[PDB]
Length: 251
Length: 174
Length: 127
Length: 78
Image (cartoon, rainbow over the protein chains, first blue to last red):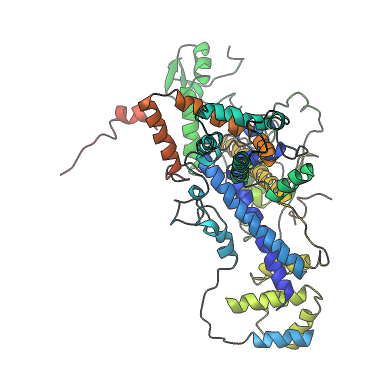
């Protein structure tokens, strides 16, 4: 196997993917904008577009139609898997990167001459494998053939509304179970959570004693939830980057 | 009000007219021969020539005319003003439009005397039109020069074989 | 088409390194198989592609690509932007053309005043 | 610590939800019901509708003549 061909096909596929997620970012700029905005508040350095662009939902001159949340998120997770593929290919590629032989192979190319068949399926099956609306007959499902079995409802509950809200009622229940009473209302519970927005309150004005078992367990479960929710609602941002950032800040 | 022109009588058998439509009938009245209107005075006429009906009948006649009428090639080099008078008009009014060429049959002329040959007319907004007689039935009439790219511009002739050096104001045609 | 594809891509593989092995093969064998070598044969064009591509693989051999997620995203955004720009150029062009059609259709081709009687592609550039 | 920083990064969502809570809370029966209906519909709806737009980008004849002449009037020869 001539590595040249393999590395070629790799660079080509990478190109295809970049082109796909670029077409996406084109039809609905929000996809990037949304993402980028969040990124802005995690990695302060990040440069973000002109506000006007964001609002008018335009990238250059044309203002694009506003899309609903479920679709934006969907395409963001699709682009997520795309970027995964890309990262993989980039990896394998990094790990992979006369005349008598020319006639030698050209001779064997004569093999099986009677192969009556039309072959238009290398760049078309890929281009197609990664494009908008690749599932239905013509135009029914925005999802590409690549991620045809991608379903957000298996990632978000109904009360979260694809990142609009985070369902904390459950944790209010567990909390009631933790404080061993009922003096605590959903709103008073949220008032409790607010402590964790401050850099010092959750530490110096704790709801319960921070050495209490029930409390520490609860806090664990809740923390896990908030984190998974975070990365769930912002697929496009590099999860590992954020994780490592936080860890280093911690140490 | 007439600006001194002699508006001719309808029977006089045609001195290019300022316009060319207005006449005077066997009586003395003034008439548009396009629109078949009768006018009392020069003041009325200038209202008509500036009117929306006399606009239309020119367009209708416009269409009505526009629906009927290894070798050697020719090359023309037309030069234009050197920023002498074009300094007073720069309001992006077709200023971006380059000169245009068209092949006209002599079958139609202001005098209609002799005819039977073609002319390679070249036109630009301010400057006056220009013509070049083409006795040869066909010269340089090529066959798929470029690889069929479709920006019609005005016509196959213009895109196919014209160049407009707009920076120097030189129009080449071949 | 697997045959054609394979021969194009192979002669393209070799043509990418030396360009001398094919020019010798053509004179040695004499087969109507490599008829795509001449720019006459349509497929030739796609050939010019493949070779280029292979020529490209020779570019960063010994160099790894270390693009990160952030970067890839930024890039795809910039590509989008480009596409939008190009689209705008196309639009403008269409407009100008429209103007031209209007004026051409709207000038007197009977205001004659003649005088006498009787490669540009490389010229319509700049140098 | 993670709960801390992640909740900080999600301040907008936290606020958004707290708001939601207060709203639903101040609803009536019918109101709360219809709202729930809405959340549900949003949940079980196609991400792309058969009635969406593609390519709707923004930026940044002789009528009385045929009646007068008597044409374009329905008639029949048997």
